[PDB]
Length: 341
DNA sequence: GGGGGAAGGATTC
DNA sequence: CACGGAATCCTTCCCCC
Ligand SMILES: Nc1nc2c(ncn2[C@H]2C[C@H](O)[C@@H](COP(=O)(O)OP(=O)(O)OP(=O)(O)O)O2)c(=O)[nH]1
Ligand SMILES: [Mg+2]
Ligand SMILES: [Mg+2]
Ligand SMILES: [Mg+2]
Ligand SMILES: [Mg+2]
Image 1 (cartoon, rainbow, N blue to C red):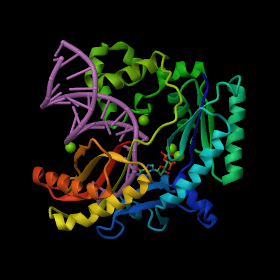
Image 2 (tube, chains in turn red, cyan, brown; image 1 turned 45 degrees about the vertical axis):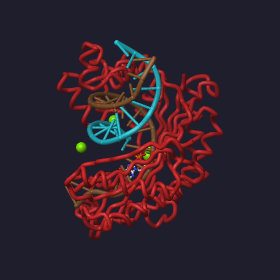
Image 3 (cartoon, rainbow, N blue to C red; image 1 turned 30 degrees about the horizontal axis):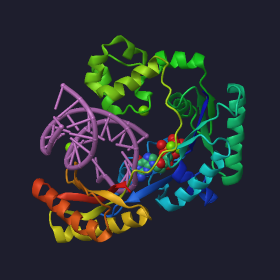
């Protein structure tokens, strides 16, 4: 099997550059403004200029301003990035029917048939990069290997505007050389847990009682890491299906007052239902972020689909359940729909 | 004992 | 000072054959 993974470079920012070359060369930071005051919120992403000085997805916008007071700060326009992405995705289908869009800017393609070896794959990669750049003016990085995981790692190593192939030889080397923290699906929480166990590399998972591993990080994550190291990981490329549609917003100020929270909640329901399109959900969860940035939720699954009126009333109930069951003020409130008919 | 959900949370990206 | 959207996974609990 030969997998070719593609990931758009600093995507949201670069889309902004495409729509405004004047920005190119300058540091760009796409932000998600919350409105609790101004310049409150987080950074969705930033071009590489800006990342050099530490401005990156996740950090508070105020930190960014601090480090780069004169970089350009643009509000995130997701609809636009989505439509550009959808276009690029269609373009990618033309290289394989077997395609897995894993995020708004990445996909894994199974080109085992289309190509005969890594030499051609690399050429198919170039073809793809050029096609995308040519057609959409978007640069992307490509990763190619025997399975999705290593394809992803390949592109991570070649970022930005790169393309890399990790052959069976290199896969054997990485299993022994790659810091397990650089392995997809392993965040800072599982990373540290792996160290308390002495594991710093994939191979290390082969020198510990499964039951112990299964103990520390759960069976799923254990079998995942083990199969990878056993060079036996082989998950296929499959079309992913939306299972949840929701929305969540930040309130101007914290609160435990229902009438003060409702307009935010209802706003989130309207937007969610719009996104539902013609999908009918049988489940709904109200999600709340408390003052201490903790996340709490309460939901319910109906035997039938949920109408907007029903979601309106049921959501207030679930919110009341939250407020009655949690003494903390609420910072962010949202709703999520799932289990579509 | 174990199937079959469901609910609430945790981790990752 | 920290948004937002979703998937997957884990634990707990309940109904009952
Ligand atoms: N709002 C928000 N959006 C994010 C976050 N992380 C990623 N995104 C969005 C915007 C990113 O451009 C896009 C693609 O993520 P990547 O993981 O591909 O980062 P990006 O493409 O920006 O840079 P890259 O070349 O992949 O290293 O997804 C986040 O933490 N918050
Ligand atoms: Mg990217
Ligand atoms: Mg990506
Ligand atoms: Mg990782
Ligand atoms: Mg918690």
